[PDB]
Image 1 (cartoon, protein in one colour):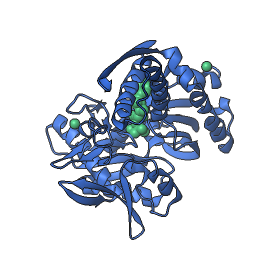
Image 2 (tube, protein in one colour):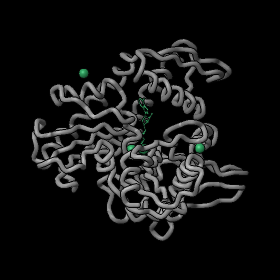
Image 3 (cartoon, helix red, strand yellow):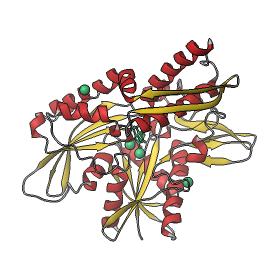
Image 4 (cartoon, helix red, strand yellow):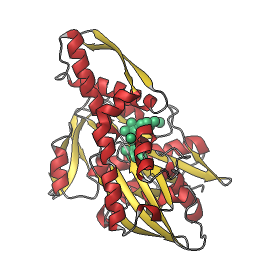
Length: 378
Ligand SMILES: Nc1ncnc2c1ncn2[C@@H]1O[C@H](COP(=O)(O)OP(=O)(O)O)[C@@H](O)[C@H]1O
Ligand SMILES: [Cl-]
Ligand SMILES: [Cl-]
Ligand SMILES: [K+]
Ligand SMILES: [Mg+2]
């Protein structure tokens, strides 16, 4: 006490605490309200969060991310087998269970997905503690509505290992609805749609709420669609640009590409607020600096297809919920990618002008709700 709410995301995590009737989204040591769900291993240390992602470009093999794509799954799992091909780190099989293998202090080591995630939760726990100036023990941790028992169990174990007493595992969409106070009894049932576009996944959930009780009507989306795909479209655009101006292709330089990706991710965030953004990278390739810029319009074209496609899962969710657009009482934005103006237009146009619940930072909405629920449970 106080107990906190932690959003353990695929790419970013967020922790909040509810005090004096208000939720405080807690900033980390670097002043960031969300922290990368990254962990890195080196000859001398173990890095978590910002410190880990900041060195991902020079240490691709021992920097782990996406642990949430493995958590609660078996090695033989089809999705595990597919994802493994795309990760720079190794995933091994231990008695039918996946484990990430890395080099730490010169020796080989493997960790279960819940162990990597416990490291991320420990970081969030310490972040809350630095702010509260007290020890944090109780917490509510979130999971996608589609997680099964094994995944929920593994996420809870990750918390226990982090030294947290998990009060409860709740679904992200429900946490988001709770953040907006949509769980208050108000007569009859209400249909709420959660549009969650994160950095690596896209989830659309339709909930029916009556008497403070939630009913997941349907879920839709794409487990391999997120802000990270928008960054790639930008990376390819600039690889071509650098090639035209310099007669050089930086494609095979893993570090140069990762550093360009990082500059694009940052330019992207700026484009949600401004109509243009500057990209300036020192010594990108062979000592050549890359100073350029990109417009919001340009950014939207490079991603027009991906953006527009987010509406397919929305139509399917409605169909599976046996509901029509007009029957949705509230539309909630979750995920940092929903801060993109063009995406808000697409969703809004689809719902014929209906206003979107977007006052709470989408990438903080889940942690916000979990923080509210954690206080209640305490
Ligand atoms: N202002 C912004 N505009 C566009 N994208 C953003 C903005 N802020 C954060 N993002 C993106 O949101 C994604 C992940 O954050 P969320 O907070 O969505 O994480 P997670 O993937 O774990 O759910 C990233 O792709 C990140 O670049
Ligand atoms: Cl930190
Ligand atoms: Cl449009
Ligand atoms: K998150
Ligand atoms: Mg998320």
